[PDB]
Image (tube, coloured by chain):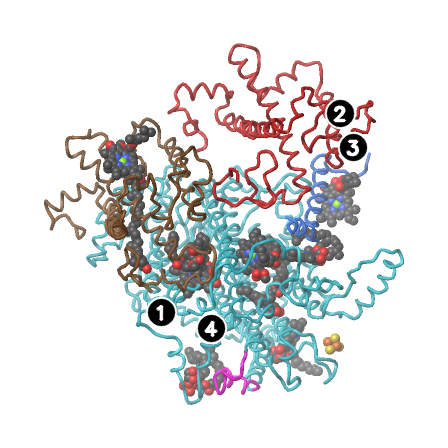
Chain colours: A brown, B cyan, C red, D blue
């Protein structure tokens, strides 16, 4: 059933979750289906594309002389998992920032969900004049618009398909990387860049086998 | 193999809540008699009778089972919560031997505060006998905050389980194909559930429970204990307790597993401090159990062209004497739920019986063997649960023969050949019961008659015509002398019941060798009498459910019917339902003596306070001499041990004195239903309806006496409840007031 | 055709939009029947109007206490004012219960039967004391002619409800950030304005 | 909601509300006024 029309189709579905036989009826139903799984693949990718860039950027810039070493700290010692460590000097405590996080996000996320349940629904109601930017598209993962694609890149359809899968190939790689950051940290107890600096120095001596 | 689901089959609304009886065609009309009410609550969960579709029956079952889990999880969370806020766990943890548990404090209205007894620990409440305190200590739990969080987790998971039952029925319900993928269930339920679940517990045992219980047994105060997360983060702390942790998973991947001998052990026996199993041994057990179930889960074929297929296995084990054997069973078990329910209940009930034996001799939790009320309550509980479950197999197997039996699939099969020599089964089994009841119970009457006549030399006893169980005695020594020869690496034996020395804890013995004699011979043979008979009643009902010589057409009458009629001299209680109704009385007579065997034996020969000069048992070791006579069971067990219950008025055990009486009322009350019949009562109601009619106050729903099968069910229910609740009061009051 | 509590959600069938402060918010399907809907709109307004009347009393005193005036906290005010009063407790309660039973009962029978209290029995009053709508009387409770215009009456109904929902949320606030801080509401305000980043609900020592 | 109120009007649900009333009434009448036997 994998025709290959999709961007990131390379014929790898051993367990057959994307088949159209499952969820035969019509309705909302369950989450295992082509409409939701295709959507969550890029969402896990985009969030991971941001995370893997940010988990290693302060450490690299810290080894370099640009950023102060006080701020340059391992991604797991910056406030998450306070047993690991906690940055004392922010402009506010973590829990105050979490309420900022929960609020400003839960607008963004639930507004996106209603567009999945009811396309174009968020433009119809008044939202401080920002309604023109949320018109959406046929595919919810790639809405586009005056903001999300403010610089219209793929005016041609063929160029979009090339970009639509470069978003995935560069993205599915990042998901693996973050899985490496978590596993590296537990065993090594050090940042991801310092672990690289060791394998380049003593590869045979610094390794998972060790 | 693949996933298959049907979206939004059923709309969710309260429309059918207002219309009771919608599931059945007969009940959807409405009530004109009061019999409609009893049939409603009865036929509610008989999904096979509602509709012929096997798919809908599967959707209903898979979603109802989610309900029992949610019902369990709020019950389980209640114990954790009630143990956190209304208990003395922190006090008992610091002085377990002297302080008694309690988690059910009572409110102060009329009387009812005296039940809050002086338990100890600056606390007063009801004394529990469920063994939660020893369970929470076997795992690392020092504070009440851990119990609160554990309770909130259960409510969260329980709502998810309830949510799933709605989702996987009302919104997105699987298809019949998804259910018939049987080979994937065993693969997932062996490896995933039993395999990883045991492996995970070893993670909790290894990383948390072992160090915490090591410090607690070394006299350290609970508040000074490092919290269990500290052992995870700090490799240095736990290394001080078990130095093997310093190496850090290099021994595992290099296959040098001897380094882990510090905390993975084969000690055997019991802990001298706690009177419980070595916690290091259990982590090794559940670890090896995981590797065993993991390989078992990679057996079948599911999708990747490797593995076995259950159908080819079954239809390949054939024999001459059997003919066509095991052939048409894969079609049975994949099509009828009742067949599986019969098999599973049989081995889920016989397992709880195995749990009851294998805990009392091998106390896994600390400070359990010294809590005699707890050790006696878990045995009695998990045995009764086994008897009910086993009897359910005889009921839920006869339903298969009546409803889901197609003779076309079964020709010269194992199931067909069993029916064709059924009269040989019941006949040969009838002789055994008579042989045993004579040679077993007749021996008791012989001892009674000899004693009353003044001929005690002629009784069956130790000072007498001894009948000693030589085979069990040989097995006790073999398992006792095993560490020398058959299990060299074993430091000691599995339990001290086989042989050895006493293990004393808090001045009380946890376990000591049990000696078998002439009395233990008679009792172990009395149990076989009650068992071979209980099988006769159920097995007869199964084979003769579909047809008999008296009634060649029972299957058309159905599973439960009272009688065909007065003809043929009488056809009352001929159905398979009425065989189950009789088997329950024999299950009761069986386990009631298995339980009396456990109480008098362990009080007299095992339990007691250890002094400088030996042990002083509770009943002075009178099981050997008195048990041979039935009057001994009446004098030394019933009349004697009932002193604590009867004298409970004016103390915290007063509730047991009342339940002891109320249990007798409900028992005798059942006799009205068993002895009598519907006919007398329906006429009496007519003379009562006249007065209610004379005053123009009469129900439009006509009053009708209970059906025949209902009067029989109502009897055995109030019967068993009164018979079982009496022991529940006679035991806990006897044992809580120790001796 | 109008805003909603969650954009894109289909509003219920029974909430047409004529009622004041209607945003299609009733997931429990309450007020689905006409008679219950006729009861709840009157319950919402009294729970509102009592909130406004009460919360203003708390701000007035808590401000007068912070300025210097002799006013106590809104909590533990009935305990310190009864210690030194000539009116015992019990004579003050059943002066309130007895006097409200008159009003609260007359309001009930206008609900069950509109225009019923304007018969002229009570002191010869007929044109007043008959309801204009369910929870919106007039004549005597509207001395200023601020309701004899449907254009300016329909939006005023929207302001009565919007400043009301907000008001009875605030009363839940006073309960909550009193139990945490055990201080007045105004004192909690000046602290947040003084050091907004540091003094929040996270740093009160509670709710964590 | 019309069907929910109808379910609440069934026999056992109405009986539950009755039982809490009669039982809670008798208990609170024994919580206060403890141990009555003679009626003044
Ligand atoms: C509020 C949500 C909701 C609603 C409106 C419905 C509505 C409906 N369900 Mg559904 N269902 C729900 C939640 C819901 N369900 C959940 C959460 C589950 C998972 C358990 C199911 C599982 C389910 C199944 C499996 C079936 C239905 C069916 C039905 C229909 C018949 C309802 C009926 O007979 O009422 C019954 C009304 C009750 C109040 C039942 C209460 C039962 C509780 C759980 C027992 C409590 C135990 C008690 C406390 C123990 C003490 C007793 C003591 C003696 C031991 C109806 C369309 C049936 C159907 O399709 O119609 C043919 C059907 O077969 N539902
Ligand atoms: C005995 C337990 C059990 C079983 C066998 C099933 C079986 C099933 N569920 Mg279900 N479910 C259960 C409990 C169970 N559920 C519970 C307790 C919940 C509430 C938490 C749900 C909530 C749920 C949803 C919301 C969905 C399913 C779906 C499915 C189907 C696909 C399975 C799949 O690919 O998931 C395995 C896939 C995973 C990604 C596993 C992730 C698990 C980690 C913990 C997260 C299958 C019929 C899907 C469906 O409808 O299929 C059409 C679907 O969308 N289930
Ligand atoms: C969603 C992804 C994500 C998230 C949640 C974070 C989160 C964080 N980053 Mg980070 N980062 C990311 C992606 C992400 N980063 C990426 C992709 C890069 C590469 C450019 C970086 C590069 C980076 C650096 C170089 C540093 C951080 C730092 C931080 C921390 C404080 C930042 C702060 O207060 O900003 C507030 C800043 C603003 C500009 C907000 C503007 C909005 C106001 C209202 C106007 C915080 C934990 C700092 C740190 O180490 O913390 C101590 C730090 O020095 N990040
Ligand atoms: C590793 C996978 C896995 C696991 C762990 C389970 C586990 C379970 N299955 Mg199961 N099942 C599986 C795969 C699995 N199944 C597959 C592949 C199929 C189809 C071939 C089925 C079909 C199936 C049926 C038809 C039934 C079960 C049932 C059960 C439950 C038995 C209750 C019990 O013994 O108490 C143990 C109880 C617990 C340990 C409590 C934990 C409960 C949580 C919610 C379950 C978490 C595991 C869940 C399956 C993960 C996926 C859910 C996710 C998609 C949301 C148990 C939770 C029965 C059931 O649903 O009863 C409710 C039942 O009737 N299973
Ligand atoms: C996994 C366990 C299990 C399951 C799922 C079922 C399921 C079923 N059984 Mg079965 N059964 C079981 C175990 C089980 N049974 C066991 C262990 C036995 C042996 C005792 C039986 C004996 C049995 C018989 C003899 C019959 C069934 C029947 C049925 C069906 C109808 C259910 C019904 O009427 O209940 C609806 C619910 C009730 C009737 C309420 C039960 C109330 C009980 C009796 C009172 C409990 C008292 C309480 C614990 C203590 C007193 C306190 C009180 C004040 C609250 C259904 C398919 C009947 C049938 O027609 O099968 C097709 C039938 O005739 N079963
Ligand atoms: C104390 C009461 C009592 C007694 C003694 C019996 C006895 C018996 N029941 Mg039984 N039963 C009872 C109550 C009792 N029942 C009740 C209340 C129920 C209702 C649930 C049942 C339901 C029931 C069923 C459903 C079944 C039995 C069966 C049996 C027989 C098993 C065979 C056996 O071991 O006999 C051997 C003999 C004895 C146990 C007698 C003991 C006393 C001694 C040995 C006799 C001494 C004789 C003496 C020397 C001769 C004197 C002669 C004189 C005239 C001079 C046996 C006759 C089973 C049966 O008949 O099939 C095999 C069977 O299937 N019973
Ligand atoms: C959740 C499990 C459950 C349980 C335990 C019961 C139990 C009962 N139901 Mg039932 N029922 C259930 C689920 C359940 N039902 C479901 C899911 C439905 C579908 C909506 C029904 C629908 C239903 C109907 C339609 C009727 C019952 C009736 C009854 C009662 C039988 C009549 C009787 O003996 O009193 C005989 C009573 C008298 C002769 C005189 C009146 C005095 C009574 C005893 C006082 C009130 C008792 C009170 C309800 C007890 C509290 C509830 C209790 C379970 C804790 C009995 C109490 C019948 C009834 O009238 O209930 C009272 C009845 O007509 N049930
Ligand atoms: C024939 C049955 C019977 C009778 C006549 C009584 C009578 C009485 N019992 Mg008793 N009782 C009974 C059965 C009975 N009980 C049973 C079966 C039990 C066990 C469940 C108890 C357990 C019991 C306890 C534990 C207590 C009583 C108490 C009382 C007295 C309380 C009067 C009362 O409620 O305040 C008067 C209430 C009213 C006037 C209000 C009712 C009128 C409404 C509002 C109109 C009264 C003398 C209490 C007492 O004081 O004993 C001396 C007490 O503490 N009884
Ligand atoms: C627990 C001890 C109980 C033992 C006494 C019980 C005797 C009652 C049974 C008599 C039925 C005889 C007719 C057989 C029925 C028969 O004809 O079937 C034929 C069957 C041989 O089958 P085939 O090889 O032809 O085919 C098998 C295939 O059909 C596979 O399905 O015979 C046996 O299996 C012998 C069974 C002996 C059964 C006695 C032992 C049962 C207990 C097992 C433990 C015994 C050893 C104990 C010592 C430690
Ligand atoms: C690998 C992965 C990662 C998720 C990846 C998604 C991720 C990791 C989320 C990333 C977000 C991040 C990292 C942000 C973090 C931070 O905010 C904090 C928390 C902490 C701060 O210190 C720093 C910052 C950065 C601020 C995805 C795994 C799924 C796999 C492999 C499945 C493979 C298959 O084989 C199967 C099973 C089944 C087949 O039918 C289908 C496929 C698909 C073929
Ligand atoms: S009702 Fe009584 S007499 Fe008639 S067939 Fe049934 S058991 Fe026999």
Residue at 76% across, 66% down: B705
Circle on res. B24: none
Residue that label 3 marks: C116
Q: Quadrant of the N terminus of chain B?
A: bottom left
Residue pointed to by mark 1 = B302
Q: Earlier in the sequence, mark 3 or mark 2?
A: 3
Q: Are marks 3 and 2 on the same chain?
A: yes
In the image, which residues are magenta? B405-423
Position of residue A136 measured from the top left corner of the image (x, y, whole percent) = 38, 45
Q: Which residue is mark 4?
A: B334
Q: Tell me if residue B191 is in the magenta stretch.
A: no
Residue B406 lies in the magenta stretch:
yes
Mark 1 secondary-structure assignment: loop
Badges 1 and 2, same chain: no
Marks 1 and 3 belong to one chain: no
Contact check, label 2 and label 4, Cβ < 8 Å = no
- Contact flag, marks 4 and 1 (Cβ < 8 Å): no
């Amino acid at each position: 059933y994998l025709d290959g029309t999709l961007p990131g189709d390379y014929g790898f579905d051993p367990l057959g979750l994307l088949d159209p036989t499952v969820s035969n009826g019509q309705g909302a139903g369950g989450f295992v289906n082509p409409r939701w799984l295709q959507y969550s693949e890029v969402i896990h990718a985009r969030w991971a594309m941001l995370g893997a860039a940010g988990c290693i950027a302060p450490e690299i810039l810290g080894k370099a002389g640009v950023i102060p070493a006080e701020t340059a700290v391992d991604w797991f010692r910056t406030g998450v998992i306070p047993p690991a460590g906690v940055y004392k000097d922010f402009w506010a405590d973590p829990f105050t920032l979490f309420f900022i996080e929960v609020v400003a996000i839960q607008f963004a996320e639930l507004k996106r969900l209603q567009d999945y349940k009811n396309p174009g629904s968020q433009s119809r109601q008044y939202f401080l004049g920002l309604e023109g930017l949320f018109k959406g598209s046929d595919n919810p993962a790639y809405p586009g618009g005056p903001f999300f694609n403010f610089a219209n890149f793929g005016k041609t359809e063929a160029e979009m398909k090339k970009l639509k899968l470069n978003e995935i190939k560069n993205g599915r790689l990042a998901m693996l990387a973050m899985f490496g950051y978590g596993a590296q940290a537990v065993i090594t107890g050090d940042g991801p860049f310092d672990n690289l600096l060791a394998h380049l120095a003593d590869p045979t001596g610094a390794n998972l086998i060790t | 193999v693949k996933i298959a689901v049907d979206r939004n089959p059923v709309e969710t609304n309260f429309e059918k809540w207002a219309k009771p009886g919608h599931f059945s065609r007969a009940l959807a009309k409405g009530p004109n008699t009061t019999t409609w009410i009893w049939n409603l609550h009865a036929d509610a969960h008989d999904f096979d009778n509602h509709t012929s579709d096997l798919e809908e029956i599967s959707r209903k079952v898979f979603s109802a089972h989610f309900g029992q889990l949610g019902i369990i999880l709020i019950w389980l969370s209640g114990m954790y919560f009630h143990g956190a806020r209304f208990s003395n766990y922190e006090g008992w943890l610091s002085d377990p031997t002297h302080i008694k548990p309690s988690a059910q404090v009572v409110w102060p209205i009329v009387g009812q505060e005296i039940l809050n007894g002086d338990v100890g620990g600056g606390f007063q409440g009801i004394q529990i006998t469920s063994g939660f305190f020893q369970l929470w200590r076997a795992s690392g739990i020092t504070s009440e905050l851990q119990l609160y969080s554990t309770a909130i987790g259960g409510l969260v998971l329980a709502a998810a389980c309830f949510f799933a039952g709605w989702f996987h029925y009302h919104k997105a319900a699987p298809k019949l194909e998804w259910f018939q993928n049987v080979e994937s269930m065993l693969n997932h339920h062996l490896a995933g559930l039993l395999g990883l679940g045991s492996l995970a517990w070893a993670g909790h045992q290894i990383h948390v429970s072992l160090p915490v219980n090591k410090l607690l047994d070394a006299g350290v105060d609970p508040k000074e204990i490092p919290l269990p997360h500290e052992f995870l983060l700090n490799q240095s702390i736990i290394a001080d307790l078990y130095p093997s942790f310093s190496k850090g998973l290099a021994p595992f991947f290099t296959l040098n597993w001897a380094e882990y001998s510090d905390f993975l052990t084969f000690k055997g026996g019991l802990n001298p401090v706690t009177g419980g199993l070595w916690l290091s041994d259990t982590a090794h057990h559940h670890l090896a159990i995981a590797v065993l179930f993991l390989v078992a889960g990679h057996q079948y074929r599911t999708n990747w062209g490797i593995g076995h297929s259950i159908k080819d296995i079954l239809e390949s084990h054939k024999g001459p004497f059997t003919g066509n054997g095991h052939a048409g069973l894969y079609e049975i078990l994949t099509t009828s739920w009742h067949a599986q329910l019969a098999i599973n209940l049989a081995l889920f009930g016989s397992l709880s019986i195995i749990v009851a034996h294998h805990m009392y001799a091998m106390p896994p939790y600390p400070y359990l063997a010294t809590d005699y009320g707890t050790q006696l309550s878990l045995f009695t509980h998990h045995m009764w649960i086994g008897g009910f479950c086993v009897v359910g197999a005889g009921a839920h197997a006869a339903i298969f023969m009546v409803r889901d039996y197609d003779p076309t699939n079964n020709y010269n099969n194992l199931l067909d050949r069993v029916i064709r020599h059924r009269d040989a089964i019941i006949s040969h089994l009838n002789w055994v019961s008579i042989f045993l009841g004579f040679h077993s119970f007749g021996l008791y009457i012989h001892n009674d008659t000899m004693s009353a006549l003044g001929r005690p030399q002629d009784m069956f006893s130790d000072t007498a015509i001894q009948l000693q169980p030589v085979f069990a005695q040989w097995i006790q020594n073999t398992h006792f002398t095993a560490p020398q020869l058959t299990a060299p690496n074993a430091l000691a034996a599995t339990s001290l019941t086989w042989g050895g020395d006493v293990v004393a804890v808090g001045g009380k013995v946890a376990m000591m060798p049990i000696a078998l004699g002439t009395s233990d011979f008679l009792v172990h043979h009395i149990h076989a009498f009650t068992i071979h008979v209980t099988v006769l009643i159920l097995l007869k009902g199964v084979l003769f459910a579909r047809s008999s010589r008296l009634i060649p057409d029972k299957a058309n009458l159905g599973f439960r019917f009272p009688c065909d009629g007065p003809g043929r001299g009488g056809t009352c209680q001929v159905s398979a339902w009425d065989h189950v109704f009789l088997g329950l009385f024999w299950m009761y007579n069986s386990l009631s003596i298995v339980i009396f065997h456990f109480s008098w034996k362990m009080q007299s020969d095992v339990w007691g306070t250890v002094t400088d000069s030996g042990v002083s048992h509770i009943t002075g070791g009178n099981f050997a001499q008195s048990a041979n006579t039935i009057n001994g069971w009446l004098r030394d067990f019933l009349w004697a041990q009932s002193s604590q219950v009867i004298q409970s008025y004016g103390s915290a055990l007063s509730a047991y004195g009342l339940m002891f009486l109320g249990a007798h009322f409900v028992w005798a009350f059942s006799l009205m239903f068993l002895f009598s019949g519907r006919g007398y009562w329906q006429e009496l109601i007519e003379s009562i309806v006249w007065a209610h009619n004379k005053l123009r106050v009469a129900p439009s729903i006509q009053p009708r006496a209970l059906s025949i099968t209902q009067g029989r069910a109502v009897g055995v229910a109030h019967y068993l409840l009164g018979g079982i609740a009496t022991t529940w009061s006679f035991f806990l009051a006897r044992i809580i007031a120790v001796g | 055709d109008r805003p909603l509590w969650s954009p894109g959600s289909e509003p219920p069938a029974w909430l047409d939009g004529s009622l004041a402060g209607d945003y299609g918010f009733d997931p429990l399907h309450l007020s689905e029947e006409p008679e219950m809907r006729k009861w709840m709109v009157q319950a919402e307004l009294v729970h509102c109007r009592w909130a406004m009347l009460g919360v203003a009393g708390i701000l007035f005193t808590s401000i007068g206490a912070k300025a210097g005036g002799n006013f106590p906290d809104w909590y533990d005010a009935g305990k310190e004012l009864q210690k030194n009063s000539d009116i015992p407790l019990g004579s003050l309660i059943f002066t309130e219960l007895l006097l409200f039973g008159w009003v609260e009962t007359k309001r009930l029978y206008d609900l069950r039967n509109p225009g019923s209290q304007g018969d002229g029995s009570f002191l010869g009053i007929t044109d007043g004391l008959k309801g204009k709508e369910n929870g919106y009387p007039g004549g005597l409770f509207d001395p200023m002619g601020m309701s004899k215009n449907e254009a300016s009456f329909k939006e005023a109904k929207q302001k009565e409800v919007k400043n009301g929902r907000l008001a009875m949320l605030a009363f839940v606030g006073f309960i909550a950030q009193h139990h945490a801080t055990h201080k007045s509401p105004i004192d909690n305000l000046l602290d947040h304005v003084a050091d907004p980043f540091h003094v929040t609900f996270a740093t009160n020592g509670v709710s964590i | 909601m019309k069907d929910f109120t109808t379910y609440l009007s069934t026999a056992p649900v109405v009986g539950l509300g009755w039982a809490i009333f009669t039982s809670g009434l008798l208990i609170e009448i024994n919580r206060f006024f403890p141990d009555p036997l003679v009626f003044s």
